[PDB]
Length: 64
Length: 50
Image (tube, rainbow over all chains, first blue to last red; front, side, top):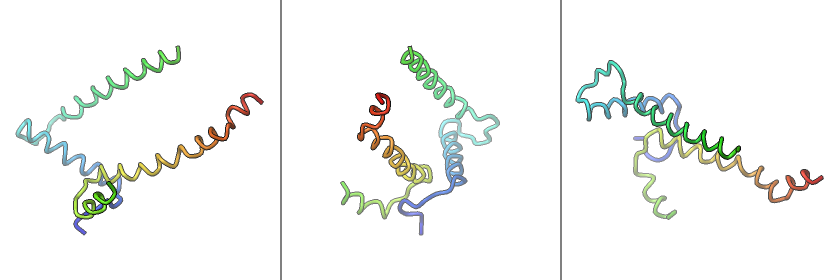
């Protein structure tokens, strides 16, 4: 009980937790939770896009 | 390191994102066994130089 240990978990629960975390992270910086638009994710995807673009150039160079 | 983990893991709490992550470590470990065993047996070199 009480969720102790390392028991298995459902994909519905993974996104569930990840949503409560995003909402709380927003509360610490914007002090509100209405979230009409969610800038937290938009700013994160821009980093993931930059990292991915850098790796693509390496494959091009490696192939050359 | 094993004795430490055996004593601490049963009384702590972990969020679903980490529990899901420890699960996938097993599948990532099974997948490379066959491609590596054939490399050790020199199969890829033997065929390419049939």
